[PDB]
Amino acid sequence: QKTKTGQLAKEKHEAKVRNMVHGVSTPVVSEIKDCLTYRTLNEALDRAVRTRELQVE
Amino acid sequence: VREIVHIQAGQCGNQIGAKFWEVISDEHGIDPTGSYHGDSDLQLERINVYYNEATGGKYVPRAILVDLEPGTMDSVRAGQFGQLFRPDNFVFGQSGAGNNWAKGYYTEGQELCESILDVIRKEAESCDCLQGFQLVHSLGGGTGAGLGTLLLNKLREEYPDRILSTYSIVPSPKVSDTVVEPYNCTLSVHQLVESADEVFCIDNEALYDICFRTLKLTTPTYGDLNHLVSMVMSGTTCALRFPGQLNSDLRKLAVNLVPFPRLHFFIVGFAPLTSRGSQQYRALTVPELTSQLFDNKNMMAACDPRRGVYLTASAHFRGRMSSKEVDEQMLNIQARNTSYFVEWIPSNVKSAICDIPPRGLKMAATFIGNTTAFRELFTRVDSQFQKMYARRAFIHWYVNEGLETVEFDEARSNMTDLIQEYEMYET
Amino acid sequence: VREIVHIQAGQCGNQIGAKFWEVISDEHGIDPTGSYHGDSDLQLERINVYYNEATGGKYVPRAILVDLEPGTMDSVRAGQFGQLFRPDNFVFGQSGAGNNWAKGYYTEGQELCESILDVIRKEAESCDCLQGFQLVHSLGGGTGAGLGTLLLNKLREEYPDRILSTYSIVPSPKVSDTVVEPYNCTLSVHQLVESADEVFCIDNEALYDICFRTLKLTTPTYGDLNHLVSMVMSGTTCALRFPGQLNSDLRKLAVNLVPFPRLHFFIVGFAPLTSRGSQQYRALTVPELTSQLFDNKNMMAACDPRRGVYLTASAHFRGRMSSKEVDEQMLNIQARNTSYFVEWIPSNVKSAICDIPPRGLKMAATFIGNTTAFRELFTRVDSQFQKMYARRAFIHWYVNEGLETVEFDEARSNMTDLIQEYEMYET
Amino acid sequence: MREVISIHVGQAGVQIGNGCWELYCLEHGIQPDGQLPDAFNTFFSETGAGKHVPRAVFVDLEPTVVDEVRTGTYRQLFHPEQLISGKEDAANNYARGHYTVGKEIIDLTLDRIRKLADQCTGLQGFLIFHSFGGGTGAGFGSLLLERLSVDYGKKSKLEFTVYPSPQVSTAIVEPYNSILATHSMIDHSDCAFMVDNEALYDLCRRALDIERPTYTNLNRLIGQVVSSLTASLRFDGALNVDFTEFQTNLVPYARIHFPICSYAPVISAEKAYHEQLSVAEITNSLFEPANMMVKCDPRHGKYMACTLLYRGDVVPKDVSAAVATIKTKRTIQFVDWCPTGFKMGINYQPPTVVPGGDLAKVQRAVCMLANTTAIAEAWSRLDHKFDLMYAKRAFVHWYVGEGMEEAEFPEAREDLALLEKDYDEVAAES
Amino acid sequence: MREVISIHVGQAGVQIGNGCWELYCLEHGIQPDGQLPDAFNTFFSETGAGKHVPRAVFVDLEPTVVDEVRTGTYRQLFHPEQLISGKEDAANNYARGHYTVGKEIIDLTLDRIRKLADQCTGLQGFLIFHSFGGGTGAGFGSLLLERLSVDYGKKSKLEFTVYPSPQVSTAIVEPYNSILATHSMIDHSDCAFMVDNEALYDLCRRALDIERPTYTNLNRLIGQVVSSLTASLRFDGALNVDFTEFQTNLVPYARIHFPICSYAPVISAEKAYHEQLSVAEITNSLFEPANMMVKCDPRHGKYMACTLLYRGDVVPKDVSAAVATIKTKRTIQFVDWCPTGFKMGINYQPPTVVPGGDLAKVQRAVCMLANTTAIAEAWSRLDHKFDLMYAKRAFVHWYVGEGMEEAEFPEAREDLALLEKDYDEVAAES
Ligand SMILES: Nc1nc2c(ncn2[C@@H]2O[C@H](COP(=O)(O)OP(=O)(O)OP(=O)(O)O)[C@@H](O)[C@H]2O)c(=O)[nH]1
Ligand SMILES: Nc1nc2c(ncn2[C@@H]2O[C@H](COP(=O)(O)OP(=O)(O)OP(=O)(O)O)[C@@H](O)[C@H]2O)c(=O)[nH]1
Ligand SMILES: Nc1nc2c(ncn2[C@@H]2O[C@H](COP(=O)(O)OP(=O)(O)O)[C@@H](O)[C@H]2O)c(=O)[nH]1
Ligand SMILES: Nc1nc2c(ncn2[C@@H]2O[C@H](COP(=O)(O)OP(=O)(O)O)[C@@H](O)[C@H]2O)c(=O)[nH]1
Ligand SMILES: [Mg+2]
Ligand SMILES: [Mg+2]
């Protein structure tokens, strides 16, 4: 016989009940680096890459 | 050796103090359990400036926590560095502060004044080489605005010779957090003018401005604002703890910056400042530091110096660097910008050098200055307070505690005299 | 040493600038990440002219990117060499200018000009000795023309001594991109005549013709069109960047070529230009370049000098060559074509030799000269400007921005005066 | 530490309290039986053996409403002491519940309140819920506040009342009870909040997707406002605001003690997926007249006080952006003598949800309290209503026989007029 | 960053919008539910999680058209607040749709469009679709522009309307509605584009290979023109053109905004296999009189405006040659007042094809927007039709009885006559 079944009504509404939480906007940004400039870290890797390629390779 | 004592107010003061003692802990290398774990012998040279040593190697700060309600003390105790403070160095009330200046100063101020002065005597009498007092408070509140000035007057009566240097946060020009703040600032400054020796002004909205313009902080938190304030106020006392090629102590700073007893309000600023991205592109040098220090986008206070003229100003440098370079840059910056300075004080600027820079930066500088631009800040509260003058009815909330209405007129008359004093020294 | 600051305005300026710094980086041998990876110490003699040095062996170009909308800036950031430019150098608005010159000058130019001026002053005072400014812009109307001339005026007010050398792409006078060009071109000429020192005129149509004729390019790409202009720019400053047997700076070029203050517009050309296939069979010598330089087809401005007469001519060379050959070839080209030069100026032709040639070519040259053939371009745009101003169509947009039609009459009066000055000096 | 006491009178107060204590039990994680499967001391008492008790007293002149709690699932939590109920309701008569019957049980109520006051070490405020139109709510509440005013004196007495709707009225003699209660509150109450049922019905119909709400939905919306109000003391926050701080900021005059309440976001369990819920967005929704918990247009007057409390991830940086954006609105008028205008509070506790709740599980929320001259619009309707029947003396004899002296009716009428004149004079710029 | 908002009015406007957003979602790779299987911020907003929302509002006085979208597959994408449905339509009466019924819903519609703009930071421009024949489209559009003109001031208001066909018609009162609208957009509209269904049918039959098109096929053709116009704002190109550029270039005066549109190639999906269709090929096809979607004679219409937006692999050199070749044609006579006369936009984004679509998969395509004096031919036809019915007062009673004053008809009649006088004066040489 005919087969026509689909329950969008629950799927839309039960999901809309659960995962309501919107807009996480995580405030994980920290200042402690800018006062502790990592430029020294980036140049440390820059020299390390420079020395490895120019000398070793 | 050259001791200082640190005092904090209820919510703003203790939170800033909490971050400050983290900052000093990193600088001197104090482990979060109070035991020294640094890497240089220079750290222990002048640790007596800020710390006492207990039997066992556990180091305890010269700090006292004052509040009218226990809300902030619980937060500080549970904090990361809450162990460091002395268990007997917590003084708190058992009533709502109510953000009221008159209520805090009179009602609970007299109840707590006797105890807090006795607790302060523990640190005051146990340090032989003491020269210093360091108060942290907010002017728009109820515990630092009122009770802070009560402590300031009592300490002045007890110890006239010691320096009374305080750090203050001013209500914001656009919107501050509380409605009655025009009253609180006007009452507090009256005591501050006569009693305090050195006053530092910091604005929250300028701190937001610096975060967006320079640091590119998409989400600046309260810790970020406290870190900038802690950076500046830690740099002031760096000369007392570390060697340098030209020292500048608190008294040197006061004598150079203060030409007259009442005009002693200071603006603060720190360099270098840069964001995550462009810090890698910066050629960090002394002329770059000079550019940042005098830059109109790096002061913690939202007051444009270009609208007025400058009184004496000072800057303190940390790091291994040339002396001639500092002298030339300050000589050039003075000759380049003649109009902003005053002729009747030759050599408007002062310089200082310290050997050891802060961690992570090869060289840093601290800017402290005085100018006529403060009059705009006083005009802001004066205009707001003038509209509050029709709300002398609203002052009925204040008189219920015991204040009389004529005090407000006395305070505003003092503001009018101070504003006219700055105007006449502009000429 | 002797520094120059580079400024790029709008859509046309930034794309030319992207190619220009690609050429300069190839010249000096700077890796796209800012590292030096060249093989010549002579590249390091005058790297300070165009570059600042950041700590850690990285070089930051003296380039400021200016626009009113972020579309071009996003394209440049995603580019191959976008990492080189300092992030804080990027200054942009949040509005399509609309190419209304009144809007781009008064409505949005004034607001942005304050930020651009301070960013300019950042690099302006960071060099040991500034000598001149380099600007790339098109005479469109929105930002390259309106804001470009505003910044040119402000820079003239700030630095009267320095040379404000601007590169201009005039709207192509047979096919072009907007109906409102002659309004913008007429006003831009009015501002550029008084405030600019050297103005270089470039036509896209001549660039198309050059590519099809000499380069044999089936589909002339905007990359190659900008590449030719970038090559001409680099040759102009090559004398300052490398030593030579006879040096010539911008001031030498400005003094020599310009007889009278207003008549200072220049046509430019480059040689050798050769197709990708037939370069193997070419016997490149000095006479070959002289034929190419003075050829009426290798010129990238669509105004045939054979119609007019020449006033001044300059020749630049790159490579090792005999000075007699340049001197003899130049005299011969002067002596034969006596019908194209003014009688009252003997030795109308100037020379210069640079030691190091551009990469890939064993020998190269650059042609810059001044002629009366510019009367055609001004007459063409004047006729177009005359028609619309008679109808007063499209002016309602400019009126809404506050520009009154009497400004157009003054601009055309200046334009007509320049045409008459060229006409009378031809005799 | 710092303790608060809640007392509920007149049906509506109790059922609102039933919603509130349901909300607080879930918020802190307390089962209805009182055991655990924090900051309890702010509202609950640890009695030992793991059981907790709320700091509240329920008093009603009829047993029906209280018997609902006694026979309900909540019964194991409340002390049988706290469930006082009378033998005979006041039946919509202010005089009957104040003189003839109120004095029969008023002494009993105060003794139980004082007994809990012994256990409150840092008692700094009270929370009282009224229904102005009710006979028990108005008559008994007036006597209780008058007694409590002299019992303790300098202690915060915050009220949460329900104003009669502009058109919806369930009591015919409601204006009689409303004015007499207002005349008694105006001298003792520190600050009384204002809400009405009709605005609750309209907001629940438009914002929430409820075709036909009941009293339960209205009470839960009220309970969320109460929870947001009390969250400053209960939990750590970047900007904690004390009860006395609300008293100083909210009522900047002598006797103006009636602010209006607002709450955002109030969104369906369905739409908010499609929306940004930004703090700037929720802040702008607060000031729109459609969201007011009182049916009065702010455009008929001006503002002189504002208080915003943020429950959620709201970073202080954006809060400054939101309030600055609000000041640019021309549709919002601020009086000249209040340049500051605002009191902010930021608390880290997210909003609390209820099983089978009518609201979405939003991450962040803000509760707004505002004092404005627009409440004078509500006064004029009550004044005109009372004058119409009293001109023909429609219900004088019922009150007079129950202990009312006829001279009291004109006295309360003039007291309301003084309130109207005081409100109008404050609105005038000086 | 840079943002646009769209409004859809009436029966016709919603259906065109239905086709457009399927085209955008397929172009941007967005499922109908809003989750991905960039330049989205120009038209869409990210509502957290992984769902998007369109920057559009659908408004009509009848629920039938809106309910179709609510029941369609795309119902998940749209926000239910964005779908506003009226109660009873204007019944093809301008007076009824402007005053009696339009004013009932105008305030609600204006609130949502302004509320949506609060999330719209880099915003300059609006898109409003109208049905000139219908009463609601003409009536509501005039009132909507009147409000938006004063609320926002100097903002780019651009309209995509359907002009009445010269002979094909479906409403007898169509000329009345068109003339009353033309009086209002002539002052409240920055620049509005129009096409007529008669030429759309003819182009869909000759060049395209559909024997009997429906409204769905015509809407798809309209959507491609809109997509080409908005292509510059979403993708990089050698010559990007902003909204302000279109307004500056296309009009030489204030009241002469009305341009005409042309899209090439319009070849079918099956006939397309034989032609390469280079730049010169498509450029020549644009200027054919038969390729207009407005049935106007280019012989009578001089050109004083042109805009050539190309999409696909296009080299600027070929365009310059193609434009130069076009200018040499004697039949295409530009006005003396327009020497340069061209704006061109080359964009690297190729066009898009829709499953079940009716368009060829062309590698490159060009959309054309120009202003010509031939539009005055259409005004004369509309003017005569209005005069014939108004001479004997054919339908005055319906408009008068719906709140519209009788004297407005000669006022709008004179407003058209001035517009035609302006076109004749501007077209004349000098
Ligand atoms: N928000 C809200 N309001 C309610 C609720 N129940 C009642 N009310 C309102 O509060 C008023 C209660 O007053 P009454 O009906 O007189 O009951 P009462 O307070 O006990 O007064 P009496 O029984 O007459 O002595 C009603 O008029 C309602 O308008 C409720 O559940 N929620
Ligand atoms: N191109 C196109 N035009 C349409 C379509 N549907 C309607 N129209 C036009 O719309 C006109 C009639 O107006 P309606 O579509 O009913 O819109 P309306 O303004 O709401 O009309 P009323 O509801 O009667 O007030 C007709 O003359 C058509 O030209 C369509 O699907 N495609
Ligand atoms: N920058 C900053 N300001 C703060 C902080 N905590 C509180 N404040 C400010 O302090 C004000 C409250 O004043 P109050 O705490 O009574 O001042 P106190 O008594 O001196 O501590 C608020 O308006 C805040 O703006 C903080 O951690 N950082
Ligand atoms: N030679 C060359 N010209 C370009 C290029 N890109 C754009 N243009 C031209 O620059 C003009 C646009 O100038 P624009 O930056 O918009 O100036 P503005 O409108 O005044 O701000 C157009 O007429 C183009 O013809 C390019 O890559 N090379
Ligand atoms: Mg009740
Ligand atoms: Mg319709």
Image (tube, coloured by chain):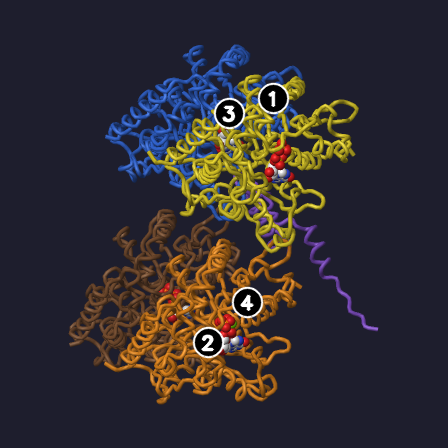
Chain colours: A purple, B blue, C brown, D yellow, E orange
Image height of C47 relative to E189, above or below = above
Judge depth for marks 1 and 2 and give the one in front.
Answer: 2
Q: Secondary structure at mark 3?
A: loop
Mark 4 is on which residue type? Glu
**Three-letter code for the amino acid on which mark 3 is drawn:** Gly
Which residue is depicted at the point 30% across and 54% down? C155
Within 10 Å of the Cα at label 3, are there few (<14), some (14-19), or many (20+) other Cα atoms? many
- The residue tagged 2 is E133
- 1 and 4 marks on the same chain: no
The residue under label 1 is D123
In this view, the residue in front, D215 or B54, is: D215
Is residue D117 placed above or below C301 in the rendered structure? above
Quarter of the figure that contains the C terminus of chain D? top left
> Which residue was labeled with disc 3?
B98
CB-based contact (under 8 Å), mark 1 and mark 4: no
Note whether ligand 2 is within 8 Å of mark 4.
yes
Inter-mark Cα distance, 3 to 4: 57 Å
